[PDB]
Length: 219
Length: 105
Length: 109
Ligand SMILES: *[C@@H]1O[C@H](CO)[C@@H](O)[C@H](O)[C@H]1NC(C)=O
Ligand SMILES: *[C@@H]1O[C@H](CO)[C@@H](O)[C@H](O)[C@H]1NC(C)=O
Image 1: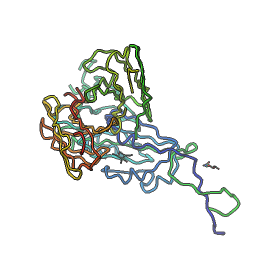
Image 2 (image 1 turned 90 degrees about the horizontal axis):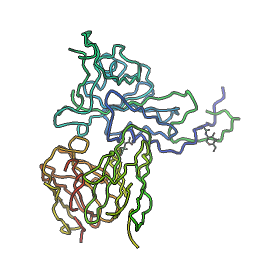
Image 3 (image 1 turned 60 degrees about the vertical axis):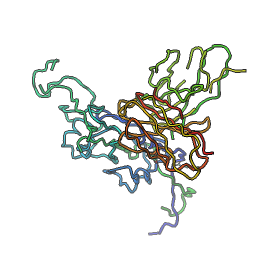
Image 4 (image 1 turned 120 degrees about the vertical axis):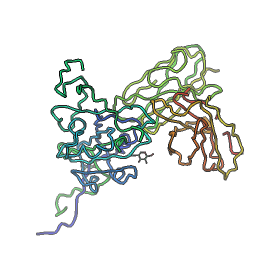
């Protein structure tokens, strides 16, 4: 065969900064009941910054390797951001057996992305009392990936006759991730879900190099 | 990062109402925690409100606020305290603060 | 008690550290219901940025040169060094104690 002599690097004409910091430097995070799933599109993403941040305790990739990312153009990237408690940090993972993924945030087993989390006990923490983050104890379906179950009602989870009025059927008012103290530490989890070319791509790094000749053996 | 943009100053002799404005970059959200202060004439900064509530003063002030880039603006008379009294702050990212008003000539 | 502060004016050499203290009536409150203490800094009629201090921890914000003995109702900010003319007026803020309140050092000399 004939060895290619030239190459084509053809990237979309994107001039935006790609504000991941508007997800990560936030003063307020959602509880495990819900997340914003902020949509990131049309930007020059650079994941070097998140990967090498000294602020992160974990950066786990299931799909695209952490050492790549900048070389891939995605159609959309979504940021699912919430506060989780230390003992459950790894439990949102495909090993969905610890009673968080099935009542609270569930990562897909075929997740294409990466999960970021960090110790943050100088924020979202208290000297004492309850705080802003609760939990879910039952669902009776064990949830779908990315489902946001925010329905709070007295429910006969225990098959005890709480017919509207309350027992082990009450609200899951757990008070997690802050208790003045692992098992009381907040971690601000951000999950980045990636769309693997299902439309013209809009999110990728700072590359370009071509004349689009189309008449040479090229890479 | 999350820089706030103001307008020019507003000069008025009569006790007419005035409107000011604040603009910024961003995405939509349920969170609404932007706020306002005044540079009081011989005091430090003083807060009028944040979420649409008032600090210890008469509610002659208007919380014209929205989601995303909150179209933040506001008083009915301007009969007192005109010394650049509308600084904008955004307690969402980096606690950014920035800031206007006058009765003269 | 009233978020009052030490009247530091010009008594800092251009190559020296400085400190400013202020007094509150209590120590564990904020605007969001958590613990906090805030600082702002500017000389001219410009916009100071807001720096967050905890009741058990140190911060950094836009500027790096911060430390401070926020040990009790008497809360002190430590200026590691005042770099000559790079000065400004300092204010204390407390969620439950007027949010911003204080007297403001002044200059280097
Ligand atoms: C980038 O711009 C050039 C024209 O300057 C265009 O030919 C190229 O196709 C654009 N990139 C992509 C992926 O379309
Ligand atoms: C968060 O803010 C810091 C400045 O305090 C900045 O260095 C960092 O890059 C920001 N994080 C992201 C993901 O942009």
